[PDB]
Amino acid sequence: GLQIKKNAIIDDYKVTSQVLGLGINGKVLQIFNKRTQEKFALKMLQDCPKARREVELHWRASQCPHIVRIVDVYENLYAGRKCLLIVMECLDGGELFSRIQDRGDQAFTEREASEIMKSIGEAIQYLHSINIAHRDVKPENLLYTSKRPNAILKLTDFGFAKETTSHNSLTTPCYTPYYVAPEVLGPEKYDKSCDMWSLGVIMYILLCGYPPFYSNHGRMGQYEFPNPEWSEVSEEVKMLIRNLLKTEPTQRMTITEFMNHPWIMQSTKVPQTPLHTSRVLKEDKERWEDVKEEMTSALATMRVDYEQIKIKKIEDASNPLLLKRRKKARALEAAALAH
Amino acid sequence: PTFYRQELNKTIWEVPERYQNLSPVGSGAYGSVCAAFDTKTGHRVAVKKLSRPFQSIIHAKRTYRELRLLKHMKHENVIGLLDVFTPARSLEEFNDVYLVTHLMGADLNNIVKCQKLTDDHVQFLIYQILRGLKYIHSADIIHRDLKPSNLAVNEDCELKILDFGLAGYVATRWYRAPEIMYNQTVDIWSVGCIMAELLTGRTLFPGTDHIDQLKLILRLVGTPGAELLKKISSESARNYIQSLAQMPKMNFANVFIGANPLAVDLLEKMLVLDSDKRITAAQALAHAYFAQYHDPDDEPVADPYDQSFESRDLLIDEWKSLTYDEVISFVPPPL
Ligand SMILES: CCCc1c(C(=O)Nc2cc(S(=O)(=O)N(C)C)ccc2C)cnn1-c1ccccc1
C-alpha cells in the first residue's frame, strides 16, 4: 500500500546538513517533518526497478517491530539523477555487537543472548512468513534504536532482499549411492536458507565472542566449540547451531523450527549463565573488523547473485583466446589444402 | 590529474574524472568495488578501494605485497592492473590506495548454482584456469585460496583468476588440499575440486568441521599407504588417519557417472593424495581433454620478481613509503 510521493520532498520535510553516517549508495541525512517536528534518517537510492522492488519489500516488512520503519518515499531529482528518497525511522543505538563491548561490564549473559536472537528470529520469521528473504543479515544491519536500556533491535538495509518461493525441502534419505548424480537446479533454495545460515553465525558469535570460521595460520571456531568459552554452554544450544550451519540448504534448519526450539520458544526462562563475549570482543578491534569482512565475504558464496550474467554456449561465444585458437584450426585446415 | 569526491560504499571515494558512473558491486568484502567507465581507455572497469591498508604492520605489509604481485601479473587468464591511483599528493597525505581492473560478468561460484555447464564449458574453463596457473606457477607463486568465487567469468566464457591476498579468517575451505590443513600442486588440488563441481553441480567435499573435511576427502581418494603415511608431520595426524577403516581410492568413473572419460581421467590426476605424484599445470594443458584449446606456442610463462624487502621486517611508515613508490611508479598497459 506504498504511495511513492511525486512532489519535492522539501515541501514536507526540512532536510538538514547533519550527516547520520555514510550509506552504501549515498549519504544518510537527518531531516525533520515540518508538521510534527519529528526527526528521521533519510537514505537515498537511484531510481530503477531493483530499487523500487527493494523499497516495496521493505515497506511490507516495516510492519514488523524488529524491522526498521520506512515512513515515506519520494521520487525526486537529486544531483541530475532520478532518485528514490526514503524517509526512515532514526536509529541512534549503534550496532548490536558494539553495545556488548560497551559494558560496565555487567557480564553479558545467556538469557540476554537468547532475546537478541529471538528478536532477529522474529524479524526473519515475519520476512519469511510473507515469502521474503533478506539476504544480508549480518552485524552491521542489526542496529538498536537507542543507547537507552529498553532499546529494541532492528534489521536494516534491504539491498539484497528479494521475494522468494514457498517450497517444501525434501529431507534427504539415509541410503544413497556412491555416485554423484546431477544437481536439479533450484537457485531459490539459497534464499530463505541464507537468512538461517546468518542466524547460526550471529548466534555463534553472540555466545563466545568470535566467529565459527577457520584461520589460515593453523579464538577461531572451526565449527567446534572451544573450551574455555564454551565449557558452560548447553549441548541443546550447540545442536541448534550445528543445525543452523548445516552446509546443505535443503537440509538446514527452517525459521519455524528455529522459533519453536525451546532455547527460543521459552527464552524468558533461559539459564542466566554468564558469557565471555564482551571481554573477548574488547580484546582486538582490528580482529573484529576481519570478522565483519569475512562474514560479508562468506555470504556472497551463500546467496545467489541473480544480477550476474549467464555463459553463452561456446559456439555462440567469441573472445580473443577463443578466436586465437579457432584462427589456428583454420590455419591448419588451409595449410593442408595448400601444401 | 584532478579528482572528484563521491559518497560510495560507506567511505568518501575520490577518483580521477576519467572514471565515471561509479556504481557499487559485489560482496564489498576486503575493500569495496565499484563498476565504472574509463573514458581514457574507453571500456568498462572495476575500481577497488583498499580497506584499512595501513592500519597494522601486518596490513601495511600485505598491501605492499598484494600490489607488487598485481603489478607483475600480466596474463590473459589472470587479474591484471589497468590502473592504480591515489588522491594523495605526497607521502604525508598518503591514506588510500585504489586499484582498477577489467570488469567481468559473474563468478563461477554463482554460475554453478544457476546453470548446467556443458562438457565444452568445462573444457574451456578448466583450460583457462590451468593456462593461468602455469604463468602464476612459473613466477614462483602459489595462489593457495583458489576457489570458484575467485574465478571471474564474463558472458563469452572468458575466465580470469582473481585474488592473490594469500600467496585472518576463512569461512570454509573445501577446495584446500589436505597437506595445508606444500608444493605448488596445492593449487592443482583446488582446480581438481572445482572441475568436479562444474561437472556435477555439487561441492565435491562439502565438509562441516575440519575432522569432517578430512574424512570426506579420504572417502574419495583412499587412505594413504604406509609409504606416504611416514611423510605426515604431526603424530596425532598419523594416528587419526590410522584410526580409520582403511581403504583404497575408488574409480572416479564410478563416482562421476556420465562424465567425459577424458575429464574423469584428468580429474584422477588432479585429485591424487601424494602431492609429489599430482599433475602440474604445465602437464595438465597437454592432457587430451583440452585438444581443442591446447596450443603450446601460446601458453606463456612469466619472468620472476624478487623478494626485495618482503623478507625484511619493518615499521608501518616503512611499508607505507614503499607502497607509495609502487603507486607513483606504476605504468599502464598499451591502449
Ligand atoms: C570481487 C569481484 C568483483 C569483480 C572484479 C574485481 O574484483 N576486480 C578486481 C580484482 C582485484 S584482485 O583479484 O586482485 N583481489 C580481490 C585482491 C583487485 C581489484 C579489482 C578491481 C572484476 N569483475 N568483478 C565482477 C564479478 C562478478 C560480477 C561483476 C563483476
Image (cartoon, coloured by chain):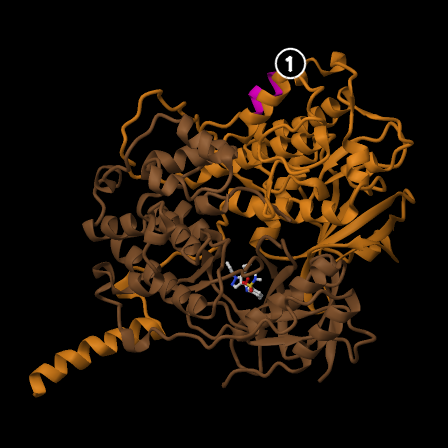
Chain colours: A orange, B brown
Which residue range is magenta in the image?
A: A255-262
Reply yes or no: does residue A256 show up in magenta.
yes
Query: Residue A122 sits in which quadrant?
Result: top right
Describe residue A18's horizontal placement relative to residue B233 as left or right. Answer: right
Q: How many marks?
A: 1
Q: Say if A30 sits above or below A168 in the image.
A: below
Q: Say if A164 sits above or below A225 in the image.
A: below
**At which x and y percent is residue A118?**
69, 24
**At which x and y percent is residue B102?**
51, 70
**At which x and y percent is residue B144?**
50, 55
* Secondary element at tag 1: helix
Q: Quadrant of the C terminus of chain A?
A: bottom left
Q: Residue at x 65, y 71 (%)?
A: B309
Amino acid type shown at disc 1: Pro
Label 1 sits on residue: A262
Using the image as rendered, state which of residue B280 and residue B34 is in the foreground: B280
Q: Quadrant of the N terminus of chain A?
A: top right
Q: Chain of mark 1?
A: A
Q: Is mark 1 within 8 Å of ligand 1?
A: no
Q: Is residue A183 visible?
A: no
Describe residue A26's horizontal placement relative to residue B178 as left or right. Answer: right
